[PDB]
Amino acid sequence: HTIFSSLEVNGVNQGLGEGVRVPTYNGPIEDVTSASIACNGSPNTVASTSKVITVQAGTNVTAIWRYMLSTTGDSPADVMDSSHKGPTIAYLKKVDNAATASGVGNGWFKIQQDGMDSSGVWGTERVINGKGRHSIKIPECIAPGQYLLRAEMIALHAASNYPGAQFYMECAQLNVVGGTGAKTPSTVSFPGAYSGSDPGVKISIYWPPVTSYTVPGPSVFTC
Ligand SMILES: *[C@@H]1O[C@H](CO)[C@@H](O[C@@H]2O[C@H](CO)[C@@H](O)[C@H](O)[C@H]2NC(C)=O)[C@H](O)[C@H]1NC(C)=O
Ligand SMILES: [O-][O-]
Ligand SMILES: [Cu+2]
Image 1 (tube, rainbow, N blue to C red):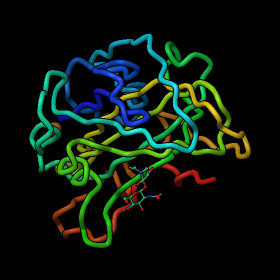
Image 2 (tube, rainbow, N blue to C red):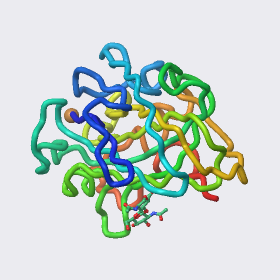
Image 3 (cartoon, protein in one colour):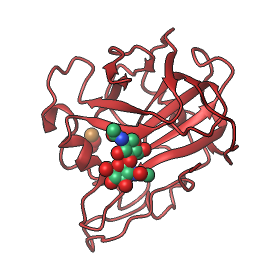
């Protein structure tokens, strides 16, 4: 239970729900076939925001994860419960109007992931124990203009069967400046990119303990 409730750009937090479409409640999506898997949604409610955040291509933005919208600290419990082990992931989608585009459908490409490292530590544990900071590089080589940024944490502690995996995601609204357009990503759809049968979705993280993890979705796009 967690929310990507603000984005840091150029080292400055852009504000709570400012340029990030935040849900009222911190619960997960569990149905990977739902329209809500793209940018969150029903049975939650997600707020619209008029802010589109300018970001220089090639630089990092940092999603700031918090337990609830009103949370005021950054200790582990202020981010997400330590039972919630799994990957962190981020995607972009080119859109016409980042303040209104829904994010459902084709156009997503993966730009970051952190599953399980060679020491058995999960991406979510780096966020939980890193003050909620989920750093994401905006590629330098993509086309400039308006995008959605979907940042996600998947908790797998209850994922031995499907449904069970818990998907926490929010979409931020970006204007990417300086992108060279030198490379056009291949894209996937949300819903569509994840299946309840995926090895990273239906998984028993303790039975036996896993030492390798396959993050769901496509490969990370690189310039
Ligand atoms: C910018 O974001 C990228 C991820 O998109 C970060 O790159 C990862 O950094 C970790 C921590 O050093 C490494 O273990 C990974 O190997 C890196 N991944 C890649 C693909 O390079 C990068 O550290 C971020 N920069 C900042 C300032 O947070
Ligand atoms: O969230 O369990
Ligand atoms: Cu939870």
